[PDB]
Image 1 (cartoon, rainbow, N blue to C red):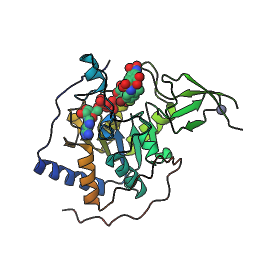
Image 2: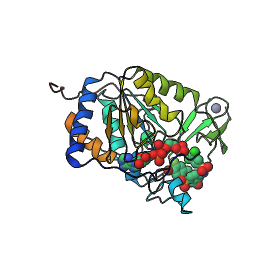
Image 3: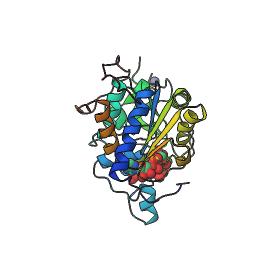
Image 4: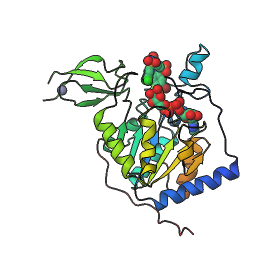
Length: 278
Ligand SMILES: Nc1ncnc2c1ncn2[C@@H]1O[C@H](COP(=O)(O)OP(=O)(O)OC[C@H]2O[C@H](O)[C@H](O)[C@@H]2O)[C@@H](O)[C@H]1O
Ligand SMILES: Cc1cc(F)c(Br)cc1NS(=O)(=O)c1ccc(NS(=O)(=O)c2cc(Cl)cc(Cl)c2)cc1C(=O)O
Ligand SMILES: [Zn+2]
């Protein structure tokens, strides 16, 4: 299944967008455990196509056209949204990040790997079949569907290194899915950014938050499978939403100094005091 492709994009008019991003700031300020869920829509503003948008991989395949890239994976820069998520984690306003993206931009943005579940894998990550050690490379490993890459493990092993890109049939990495599930169940606030939530089980994790009494925010230009469950629904460009959110929180979007891998989150930095809400 390729799900429902080419659904129309909706745009909240300016006054409604500004009110909703203020509401998003309120939910972030008032929640103790925030989880973000990202899909291909947070990388479109860096020149990587989505799957089901108007120019998505599947949408364009139906017209017998190839998807259009404005960059390579290697030369892609993290978006304002990617860098906003880095800062929210650094000041302790983001507990966990669940991504369906294989574009490798969360990792290369400097987002700590111990707070990231990459449910569908990472173009730049190969894993040793023998000892399960991961290598984050500066270039895409070159295979998809958990095939041998031609390189061997160098741990003090010679194990066969395979890509981490799931094929259609393949089940999700157990560690990442277990952590994504635990994080989603424990969150009082799940925020989805640039995902249609059409792929199971990735797309249902934000519901785990709702089922347990937490709130759900969906940010997406197209409608999503779970629109009916959202406490707040924002139809706008994620970069515009996240830059306005960061201005309300009084946080800067940090500079990206090129590809940087952070295995373990650093201690939390200071953040502005919270406004008096109502
Ligand atoms: N800048 C933007 N701002 C907001 N929404 C956007 C933007 N750009 C696109 N969108 C929306 O972003 C949404 C992107 O939805 P989909 O294309 O389904 O991507 P996924 O990540 O959820 O696909 C999941 C898996 O499916 C595959 O099989 C792979 O395994 C993927 O991991 C659309 O609804 C766009 O309207
Ligand atoms: C490889 C890739 C991953 C992405 F996330 C995005 Br966007 C784009 C690409 N490149 S692509 O043109 O769209 C592209 C798309 C599909 C395939 N093969 S596939 O069986 O249909 C497939 C790939 C992936 Cl990552 C996930 C699934 Cl669920 C299925 C190859 C390429 C290519 O590059 O040769
Ligand atoms: Zn090994």
